[PDB]
Amino acid sequence: FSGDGRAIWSQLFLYDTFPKNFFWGIGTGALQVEGSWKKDGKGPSIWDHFIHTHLGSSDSYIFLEKDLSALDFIGVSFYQFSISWPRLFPDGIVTVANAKGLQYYSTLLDALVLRNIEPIVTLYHWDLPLALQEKYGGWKNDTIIDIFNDYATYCFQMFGDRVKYWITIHNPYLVAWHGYGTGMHAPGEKGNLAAVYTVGHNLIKAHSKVWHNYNTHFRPHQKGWLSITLGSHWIEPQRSENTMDIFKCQQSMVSVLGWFANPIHGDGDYPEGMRKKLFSVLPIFSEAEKHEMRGTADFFAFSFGPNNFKPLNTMAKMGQNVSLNLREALNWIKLEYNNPRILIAENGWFTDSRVKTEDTTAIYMMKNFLSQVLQAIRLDEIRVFGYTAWSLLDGFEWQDAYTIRRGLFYVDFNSKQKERKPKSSAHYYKQIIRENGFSLKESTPDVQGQFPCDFSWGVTESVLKPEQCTDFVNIKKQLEMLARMKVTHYRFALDWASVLPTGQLSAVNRQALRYYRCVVSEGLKLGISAMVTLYYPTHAHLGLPEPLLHADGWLNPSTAEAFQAYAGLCFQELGDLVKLWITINEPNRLSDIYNRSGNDTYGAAHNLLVAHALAWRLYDRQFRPSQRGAVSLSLHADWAEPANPYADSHWRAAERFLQFEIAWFAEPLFKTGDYPAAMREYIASKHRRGLSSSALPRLTEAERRLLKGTVDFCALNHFTTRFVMHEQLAGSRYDSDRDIQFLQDITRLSSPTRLAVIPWGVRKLLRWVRRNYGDMDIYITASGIDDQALEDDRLRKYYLGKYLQEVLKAYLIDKVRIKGYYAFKLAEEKSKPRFGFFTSDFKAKSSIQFYNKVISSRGFP
Amino acid sequence: VQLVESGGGLVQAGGSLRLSCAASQRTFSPYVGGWFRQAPGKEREFVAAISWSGGTKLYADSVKGRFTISRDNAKNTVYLQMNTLKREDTAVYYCAARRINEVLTTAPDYDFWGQGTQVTVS
Ligand SMILES: *[C@@H]1O[C@H](CO)[C@@H](O[C@@H]2O[C@H](CO)[C@@H](O)[C@H](O)[C@H]2NC(C)=O)[C@H](O)[C@H]1NC(C)=O
Ligand SMILES: *[C@@H]1O[C@H](CO)[C@@H](O)[C@H](O)[C@H]1NC(C)=O
Ligand SMILES: OC[C@H]1O[C@@H](O)[C@H](O)[C@@H](O)[C@@H]1O
Ligand SMILES: OC[C@H]1O[C@@H](O)[C@H](O)[C@@H](O)[C@@H]1O
């Protein structure tokens, strides 16, 4: 009831699919798309006169077959369109009907029925016959009520055999408000306060008269439904939870939607606040009229698009903040008007007219709207039963004319043929309808089976600061945590500066080496083997010993020689116990430290590459024969998909992302000893065309021999899948040279820090790795997700189960040589994102038992 | 539907009459109410018609300004108020009904007809 909506201003969402029998559609309005404004006896409308005095169409009237083909491509269950009143009755009164206009709409309705497309027909989408404006004053004159009912009666008689869904008026708020308040819409009066509310009143009474007409004379034998399309914006308090601001949001909504919806869907009178403030000009419903206004709509038809947000004077905002939150608007409707059945009769946004077919932003607007609708259905139990995408094709957009585009199909208005070319949004919406929701195409069923008996089950930690072995208190708590898990392997990182404070071996800190040796030997007593990372750089902790840092760090090739000496010391002091080594963690995501220029990023990375290869060759010559372990490095290896999967430039950007992320280091070390060709060619071209000053330095034949073949296995840190689009960026930094922007996909599960849970990404990655680098042994050395929960971490449990299914699918089905999985990470720190299996107070989270269960079963047998 | 006229009769020139047509329908639906008139041996002549909700009314030019057509859907009745009657108005008056809500002026457009009632202006 009135006021209940004010409450709206005060887990895991695993739904992709809309209810069975959800009704998918698309809409146009006659003025926007028909053209032929004076062909075949059509009379002029107030918009024809308004365009000709205040301000090449889609030509649907002559290209009806091209529109029907577009509908077939999309695959809608319904098509919403309006009848042009002056095309049927040139003078509005029901004297002789224009025969060619009747034939046009009749042919359209027949063609829809033959294609199994339900028509939804709007009697009035703003094109009042000019003759009625000039003779009577249009909606200002209440003789319009019988004149409009006469027109509707004819339409029920000629078309209602074939039409089961009727809309009387599209968005009456804008007819009154822009037609007579702002002057932005036909007939273009501005400031006429009395007319604004007199017009609103005759629109409401006309609607009600037509409803009773349909209800008594046509519904018994035609068995359809009739409503009216009410539009509104959404709004949020200008101060976050201020009660006076919330009170004003309610008033903003009441003033736009309540004005027409309280009489029709509510108690049958205008809202109380409006009656008081406007008791002046607001006409009065008699008590008999109130009982005849309410309940005159068989469902709630709701419009939510750019006409209720732009221009800025469209609504009284009461000082508050406009918002595109469709989910909240639907909840307000549910509260205010007592849980009605809802058709989304118009929803969409717009682009500039220069956007032709690649409308990425329309896809992401639709993703957001559709995700909000799905939430409203599933979480809020709002009875949305159908959805009208707007609009079918580009047309005339009112005062904006042809400077914006709203179609799912592109139309070149300067060509004679006006061919309807499907935009990206058309392909996307077509797939929405096919899957009745968001695509499952990349998801496969759970597989049954098991990992090898010698699969490495791991957990990861980052840098352990050094503190009998039981002396060190840090070690006790690590053992208590590992003893609660069934891992066979533990990954942790040393602190180079703790081991070698000066960088020189003559000044080794032997206490630090004793601490790390205790971690390993105590772990072995639990039956857990160590994988030891020598160097784990982060944005907060570069990890270099101070004298190397002040000698220019990784821009000084001497830093690589000092790393070789550090590595040898660790092999000597730990390598009888440690058989798995990572030289460097994610050197390819340490381009955030030497971010000055691209040349800096590429130069530092070159020295990191040399560091790794020097340590690897030292190990291979001097320590492998007596120790028989294995050495590699961990590559940051998120997956990438095109943001817009219907834009060829985004498929190229996805492959380019993998080139700059993974092949950058994997090509030299694994395969050729040199940088990937795609990356060097791309940077060169951007340099050749004057846009970047970056060069990827050429590698001597000697340096290529040093680097090639220096890994014993492939180690990958995989967390998520990024969605990427091509964009020519400015500057000569690393992120500029790769020409990539990122989008978040609202339709997928994600974490408090926006990490997307895309389980099939890891399978695609493992294929890409084997396709480009051969049948190497692969370890996933880090995999995980932050989760806000402190004990019942359901997102981590979901992540673990779904990603491990895809790993096992990579193993059983794709035959990838996957040898280990290390979960990230053992414990979280107090004010960092919560990746830990254990809380910062070493409390166990519920995902431990799930991971133990998978380890015990060796998968999902 | 059956249509039944009444109100005809004999009136002095310059006088006035009110004809009415009551419709009875076994499936009550909307209709256009029409009035035609016929002198003996002459063709049937359009007089006035009215749309279902009364927004459209048409009149023959010989009758504009003198005759007024109206309707009361609750009573299923269409009314013809005839003022300033002339001798040339003497005729049999026929009410007529057309289902499609489109106000037309020729006899073949009307599906249903009353028996007719005599109007005599002496
Ligand atoms: C509500 O609206 C105003 C915009 O008019 C927001 O205030 C602005 O906040 C941005 C930062 O987000 C600043 O750059 C602007 O200078 C602010 N403008 C003014 C006039 O203060 C406000 O944050 C919005 N959102 C709320 C209140 O949640
Ligand atoms: C409505 O239309 C008729 C025009 O014939 C007029 O008599 C009446 O005053 C009009 N009312 C308005 C314009 O409010
Ligand atoms: O602590 C003993 C170690 O000291 C270092 O300074 C030397 O370089 C090593 O050769 C030696 O094993
Ligand atoms: O590190 C494992 C072994 O390597 C040998 O080459 C050392 O000289 C041994 O003393 C040591 O046990």
Image: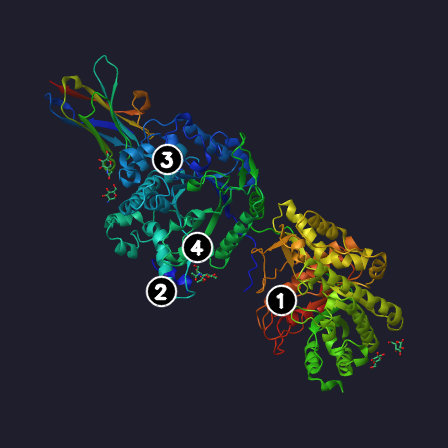
Query: Does the beta carbon at disc 1 come under 8 Å from ligand 1?
Result: no
**Residue under circle 3?**
A53
Q: Chain of mark 3?
A: A
Instruction: Give the CA separation, mark 4 to mark 2.
Output: 22 Å
**Residue under circle 2?**
A244
Contact between marks 1 and 4 (CB within 8 A): the answer is no
Inspect this view and state whether residue A189 appears. Answer: yes
Query: Does the beta carbon at disc 2 come under 8 Å from ligand 1?
Result: no
Tag 4 or tag 1, which sits nearer the N-term? Answer: 4
Residue nearer the viewer, A657 or A802: A657
Count neighbours of disc 1 (C-alpha within 10 A) and say few if under 14, some if 14 to 19, many if 20 or more: many
The quarter of the rendering in which ligand 4 is drawn is: bottom right
Q: Amino acid at mark 2?
A: Met
Q: Amino acid at mark 3?
A: Thr
Residue nearer the viewer, A741 or A431: A741
In this picture, residue B115 sits left or right of residue A452: left
Tag 2 or tag 4, which sits nearer the N-term? Answer: 2
Q: Which image quadrant: the C terminus of chain A?
A: bottom right
Instruction: Give the CA separation, mark 2 to mark 1.
Output: 41 Å
